[PDB]
Length: 294
Ligand SMILES: CCCCCCNc1cc(NCc2cccnc2)c(C(N)=O)cc1[N+](=O)[O-]
Image 1 (cartoon, protein in one colour):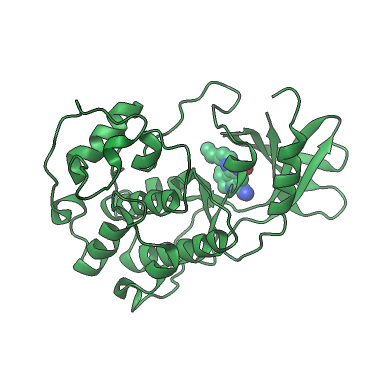
Image 2: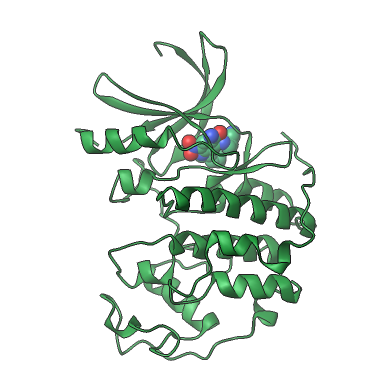
């Protein structure tokens, strides 16, 4: 490294290998993501560079975009743990409701900020939500999906998780809206509460059908235009909707109400991050300190 010193391999992210590294000059510790494949579209360089200006306390800071030796590296502020690991660690006892609420509230503030700046995440998942010892949680990888248009894979054949994908994406809609992020966050909220993924599909159709089996197969009444979507098939089985009381027990009615609005089928009916922040569920929100073992 011309200015870094690898501390260790943090993982093999969706867009390449990630290392924890120390800037030999500043001494700062950062996350360095090597971007995957053979060309690096200058279009992406400009778009990514724009994200360097997207600063908010609940968004992982993109410190630098390094395009040298015809390679692309993203330098991000470093956080010690992701929500997936934290949820697994809290599996026996569950994350306390006050902390679940604090995290959801913070994540919505982060989304409201990005969305007001016309930046979508598109691939939110527990592994992309980073936490620290202060009780903060931050969204990582905002805007990379668009800047890199197509997703595909990482670089070492890894199974893309579809668990948090909004139904309009699964039905082949080519135009994503801010609503896809609200859907993903709703799925994560449910998972924090129950300690089980809400819709753990293992294929695109299994993902879609798991959603239908829980929320009911969508129709023109609840989702105008759904039957004209690219991958919609009249042959889809028609399942009845289940009650949220059975989906995320023992979450209270304020929580079920908010989740239901985050999971509406019609992206246009789905609650916005700004509106969600005003939901009665957050009347008593606080910022607890999590028990983090690093
Ligand atoms: C099995 C762990 C999966 C990590 C995959 C890489 N995922 C990332 C994880 C991060 N930190 C949380 C963390 C997690 C584990 C160890 N140490 C720190 C960070 C960051 N900004 O600090 C960035 C990325 N990433 O995507 O650039």
